[PDB]
Amino acid sequence: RYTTAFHRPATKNAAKAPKYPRSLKANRNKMDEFSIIKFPLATETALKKIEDHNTL
RNA sequence: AAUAAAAUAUUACUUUGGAUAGUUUAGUUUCCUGGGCGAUGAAGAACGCAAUGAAUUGCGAUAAGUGAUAGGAACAAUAAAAUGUGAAUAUCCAAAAUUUGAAUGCUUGAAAGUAUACUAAGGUAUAUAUGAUAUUCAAUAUCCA
Image (cartoon, rainbow, N blue to C red):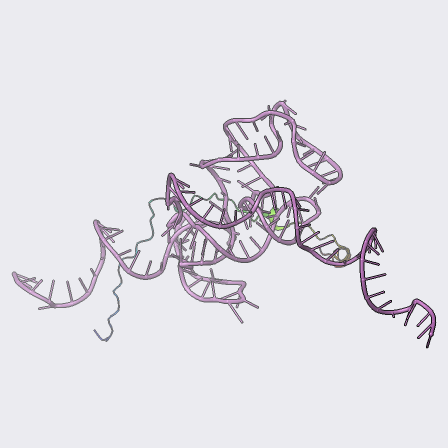
């Protein structure tokens, strides 16, 4: 056979087919555009950059 | 010999201290009823959430609270709003339940992380041992055309 090693033969690998859902968690993303940004920084230092550097 | 500053003695009042007396939403012991946790993720730990909170308490991205069932007019430190078209309050109920932790895809020091499959992001599954069933195989191990 031209090889001195015996490995585990390849067998059929079926894909997972569960008979009932594992989790029923509702499909709602809790990290949306509203929750990501809490509020702008309204300090004097943060208000100075909004004219020149065009930054928020 | 002499004076009473100091020194000493008693009482009243004040002071320092917190004994004594009155008191208890705290304990101790005995007895009665149970002894009702967890891969459907426990106990424990961390972080976060109140209009003004640091602890504590309650809770989990629906946050000092949501729905439902009872309940019937409050809360309060200060403002506000909502409120008999139902406020406080209670519950062996329903929804929801961040990071961890037996911790279980892999790694974890105070580590930031990360692979595949299914259903760009998000969510599920994938540890080890193990019983049953199905299925793909390995061994001339026993026969055998």
